[PDB]
Length: 124
Image (cartoon, rainbow, N blue to C red):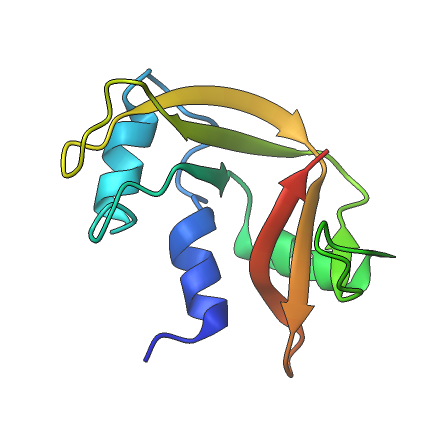
């Protein structure tokens, strides 16, 4: 099955754009990346940077994850990200999202060898 590493790329990476370009970005991307297949995923963040720069976070600032795990890492630099939150009109399978653009530090959990991001923990 899909590796934790590949799932992170599919759920969270968008190197093809610098930023969300219209209010429909989240609707289009949640759909196209297959995140609304079984249910409307309530929240999701997309990162508009090269994969190499996001992978490098695993060698940056070690921090505890929101759940208390100690394999979390925070980016030294801010990154271009898009936050997607379900709207009050969202109704499976017509999942609907509010697109919000932001520039923040990202916190990821890392695992494996190579040591790469497997979970997006938060943006700060």
